[PDB]
Structure formats: C-alpha cells, structure tokens
Length: 332
Ligand SMILES: O=C(O)c1ccc(-c2oc3c(Cl)cc(Cl)cc3c(=O)c2O)cc1
Ligand SMILES: [Cl-]
Image (cartoon, rainbow, N blue to C red; front, top):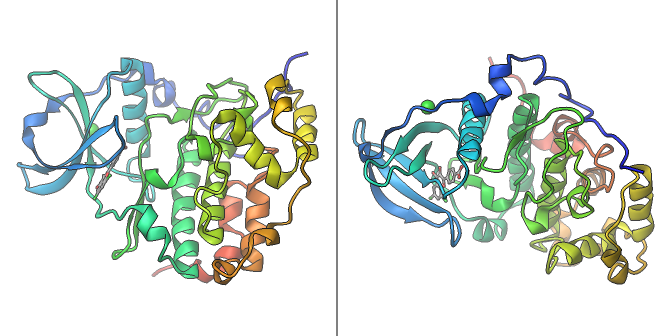
C-alpha cells in the first residue's frame, strides 16, 4: 500500500494556530520599491546562475546586498518574501531590508543586510574546536527559530551560512526553497543540495518535516570535525544514498523503508550492495583527531539517522553536552 504517515515531533500544529494570513503566502502582496535607490558596488559570488550584488542605500549610505530574482513563478517569489518577513528579527536569520524592482526591466529583487562573509572553504580549514561548537550553536539558534515559526529551510549547506569570523556573526540565508510545515502535507523531494539531501528525499518520501534541516546540519558537523568536505560525496542523487549507506549501513536503511512503507526505486538495488553500519571512530585519523571529541560523536550519531523522526530536534541538539563550552549564562 501507500507510505505510512509521519508528523513532526515539535512545532507540528503551530501554523494552524496562527492567522491564515501568516502561512497563506499566495495572498501576500509585496510592495515593490525602486531599485534605483540602491547603487550597485560589486558582484558577490553565489553560483553560476544566481546574481547577487553589494550595493549602497543612497538614502542612508548603508551597505546592503541585492539579490535579483531569477525568472521563477510569482507564487515562489511571494513565498520567499512572506517567509523572510515572518522570520525578520529572528536569531541569526538574514534580515530582509527591502523588496524592489528595476524601473526598466521590472525584475523583482530582494535587499538584505550586509555581513562581511568569509567563504566556508577557507574558513573550515582554520576553525578551532571551539569555533565549530560556537558556529554550530549559532546555526542551531536560527534553525530552532524558523522551525518554531513553522518553516522548513530545506537548503541548509555551508554556502547558505554567512559568517563574519572577526565579529563572530552568523546568518542563515537563501530562503528561496523554504516552505511552511503543515501536518500530513506531502512536499516536493527535489529540494536541498545533493550532498545535504536527507534519506527521505533520496528515497522519495514526501511527508517530511523540520527534521530534514537537521540531517543537513549533521552533514555539516561531520565535514567540520572529520575535515572531509562534503562528508557524503555522491556523484548524483542515486549514488548519494549509497555514500550514506556505506556509513549508516544497508540493513538499517531497509529497516527505515519498512517502518514507513517506503517503496525503493529498484535501481538502488543495482548500486547499494551490503554495508555494515560503521562506527564513527573509523573516520578519525591524525589530521582530524584534535576535533573529534566523544560528545561530538554522540551528537553526530543522533543527527545522522535514517529515521527522520528519531533525529534530534534543533532544540534537543542545542541541549546536547557538546555545546556546554559555548552555552553562555543568562545576561543582565
Ligand atoms: O539569497 C539570499 O537569501 C541571500 C541573502 C544574503 C546574501 C549575502 O551574501 C553575501 C555574500 Cl555571498 C558575500 C558577502 Cl562578502 C556578503 C554577503 C551578504 O552581506 C549577504 O547578505 C546572499 C544571498
Ligand atoms: Cl519589507
């Protein structure tokens, strides 16, 4: 028969308890300012397709960033704008400053606060053990906030995490794939980026929830402490599940598919093979031994689980002993 149902363990019904206007993004009507108010200064690298520029707000001469919206459905523009406005002021969420259009092209664009980011590739090579705990904790604050606001990010990855390393400031960006969580709703599995896709996406299980972002977060933790980046390096969506199964084990994969009555694409049986669940200690060697603590492995083991419902929530993750060194006492 069909796949078994599933529900988020936390924040499941929060959107139904809010006004419909909160989550009914198709009824949202943005106000499009004049993009001429922001003089572009330099282009900022965001892939071969997305066009993002640093600019100056000539009204107050403040640094901003302008993201020209790729030709996509207006429905998806409204979704991203509504989600950004619902999340504005949240901890470590990128602040949407303005929604503008170019007077000539009429192309919609988003204006964000500027953060003096350093690209993760060079940053990951110099992060200390404390840096990893600190920035993972700051990222967890953003994920717990947006989940508590009934929103899945669905594209968590190092490229979408701006870090001002000198100011110790972090922002979660790129909410163009984010969605509102509603219990029993089936979602598109063609989300996130290959290396950070959870097993539910790869096996085409559509009734997923906030725990998808927690798998992606676990992949980032694994690449930071083990220094293998990305940690699961699939050549495509099919091979990506094999890379996961070579670590978590194939028998545990089949146990997950049986629990939720998930039909496996038979092509996976051509490439999966049989693999035991590996101990996380097997990935330690001289180049990463200084970053792989007992609590780091215990947290990673509780994040990188096939069963999305058994993964730690963002809040449970924040309460894990791994973050004890960075849990600050209440101010004032
Ligand atoms: O799509 C989005 O939601 C989105 C949001 C923000 C940014 C964004 O990128 C930056 C980059 Cl790539 C480099 C630098 Cl040096 C600074 C910034 C920055 O300040 C900034 O806000 C990019 C995309
Ligand atoms: Cl606005």
